[PDB]
Length: 207
Image (tube, rainbow, N blue to C red; front, side, top):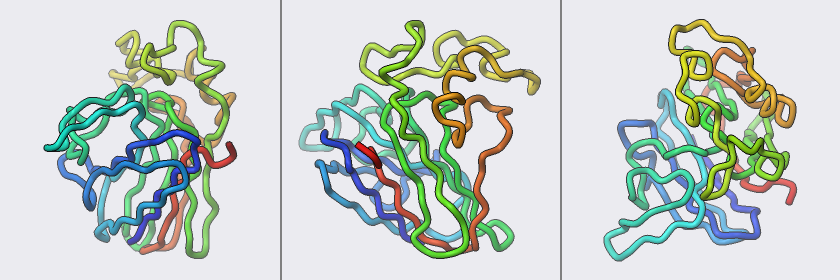
């Protein structure tokens, strides 16, 4: 399957793509404002994620640091990034279907639209100003808005016992972005698409 990753933000973003234990395609790339990066994701990929990283510095060897979404200091991510990260999530070719969603479960850093480029399903979008409105306790110094599990590490926010309810914090994300997961047991906002669809992830879709 092919993914076009488009940076419509006015600032440089460092895109990342990983399935947790391995990079997808090259795994990461600088995208200046307006730049598009097309990657090939192998069919059958389970648990793939795409996110943006902000305020990165990397050297010759591709080592450095980002203030949001750092994946252990690498330009080409092999593992997942450090929150806060708005997450585009996908499982491909699962019994003939594709499943996509946007998640705020690891916080929010960049607004995002996640849409298919082929037929038969809708896209999803979280493009509200979550950082500007972020509750004080969740504001991350490096920018972005942390999820409550990252900040407080309780069984309720992290849903450790498998039983948990919505919270004042999860409701904040859900009220600004109803189409994104706000906590781990949220009523699923997953979208079902035909198997082997193609997609576009746009950062800053509106502004």
